[PDB]
Image (cartoon, rainbow, N blue to C red; front, side, top):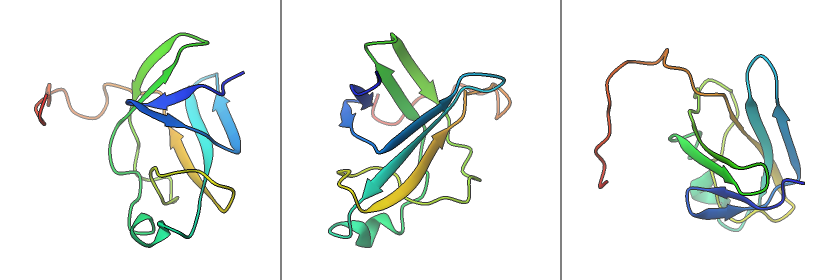
Length: 105
């Protein structure tokens, strides 16, 4: 029961968590963001890579957002309002081959 879900230190709730376990493990969780902070969030879309960590199934996963899902939104407190898509595909090495690791870590 995937209730304890963390996206890079950020604990997350959802409404419709749906992961495709075959040909491509796509973690599609429906995040219902509310109109409270939705102002900036409407501008946010996919953004970055996500470190999906789940203690139950034991998955310290770092998948990529293909950024072409045609969905919007990224994070922020899930209430029960704007059901949005954050469907993260099982990361491939298709997108570039450079170890682009240097943000602040």
